Image (spheres, helix red, strand yellow):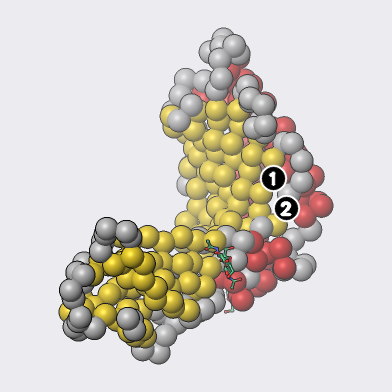
Amino acid sequence: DGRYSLTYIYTGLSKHVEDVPAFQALGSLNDLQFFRYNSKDRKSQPMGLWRQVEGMEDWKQDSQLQKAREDIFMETLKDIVEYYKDSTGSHVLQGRFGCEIENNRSSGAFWKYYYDGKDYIEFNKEIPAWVPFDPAAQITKQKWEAEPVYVQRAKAYLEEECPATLRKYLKYSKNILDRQDPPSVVVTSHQAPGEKKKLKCLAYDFYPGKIDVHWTRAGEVQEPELRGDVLHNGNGTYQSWVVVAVPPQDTAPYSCHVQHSSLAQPLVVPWEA
Ligand SMILES: *[C@@H]1O[C@H](CO)[C@@H](O[C@@H]2O[C@H](CO)[C@@H](O)[C@H](O)[C@H]2NC(C)=O)[C@H](O)[C@H]1NC(C)=O
Ligand SMILES: *[C@@H]1O[C@H](CO)[C@@H](O)[C@H](O)[C@H]1NC(C)=O
């Protein structure tokens, strides 16, 4: 088994502008986003390859949970703004929470909030208790620990519930997170009126993202003139390209080299002028 992480991020705005939802939420499994929810549509929706997955989660019921989460999250923001007596201002509250496993063993967990970009409050499950960083967080802490069970629930979420949700999602995400999709490659050239010829090597449709893409000139690795990559979440695939400029009088042989974890051995794709 390897490393898997479940991460949630909540964003609330005290005074949202037109077309921007007051509350937004998203969730990721490793490097991919699997769902989103906002206060406009009010519905938890799977994303990317999880749109094709059935039975992993009941989105209609998750929509109800997120609405409940939303209500408490925004009330927290509302209380902070009230404490500073600045409702006329535009403020933001962001919350991050989740856990991770490695070798089927819980290896991490976190739960922290940020107010206007500054650390606000975080849960330390070893105590177990919330740790305030902002003066208003002292009030929030008081409310979140009003009854003995509250901290017990928080500790249980990070230590029992979250990792159980991750293990469950992992059972339906094998063909997504554990894929070893080999890259397709395409070498292309372009001549700019007045500029040198440029050779572009593109590796696409691969996963995981880690990859080695480079050009060679007469068996000599070259220094790229332009480089880049991207991850398409809808697809769960990456693309990575490298570009080199070639002297107008150069005749040497140019070939692209691609090495990836999914390949038995590296691939070579010479360019035929
Ligand atoms: C996964 O999604 C990406 C992004 O939509 C696809 O890339 C596009 O593919 C079409 C058709 O091949 C091209 O016309 C576009 O130019 C590509 N988008 C760009 C600019 O990267 C990709 O083909 C998809 N791969 C799979 C396996 O479905
Ligand atoms: C860990 O993986 C084993 C099988 O490899 C599985 O039976 C178990 O439910 C998983 N998590 C734990 C420790 O319960």
Where is residue 249? Give x, y as percent.
18, 74
Q: Quadrant of ligand 2?
A: bottom right
In this view, the residue in front, 174 or 211, is 211
Residue 206, visible in the rendered structure: yes
> Residue 98 location, x and y as percent?
55, 51
Q: Label 1 crowding class (10 Å Cα cut-off): few <14, some 14-19, many 20+?
A: many
Q: Please state the total of marks drawn on the protein image.
A: 2
Quadrant location of the C terminus in the rendered image? bottom left
Residue at the far front in the pictured view:
193
Identified at 69% across, 40% down, the residue is: 38
Task: Determine whether label 2 and label 1 are within 8 Å by CB.
Answer: yes
**Disc 1 marks which residue?**
37
Comparing 52 with 100, the one in front is 52
Compared across the picture, whether 103 is left or right of 148 comes to left
Q: Residue at x 72, y 68 (%)?
A: 52
Q: Nearer the viewer, residue 77 or 209?
A: 209
Mark 1 secondary-structure assignment = strand
In screen coordinates, is 102 left or right of 225?
right
Vertical placement of residue 249 versus 156, above or below? below
Label 2 sits on a secondary structure element that is: strand
Q: Earlier in the sequence, mark 2 or mark 1?
A: 1
In the rendered image, the residue lying farthest to the right is: 60
Label number found at residue 270: none
Q: For the point 55% across and 70% down, which residue is it?
A: 177
**In-front residue for pair 158/145:** 158
Query: Which amino acid type corresponds to the residue marked 1 in the rendered image?
Result: Tyr
Q: Amino acid at mark 2?
A: Gln
Q: Which residue is mark 2?
A: 45
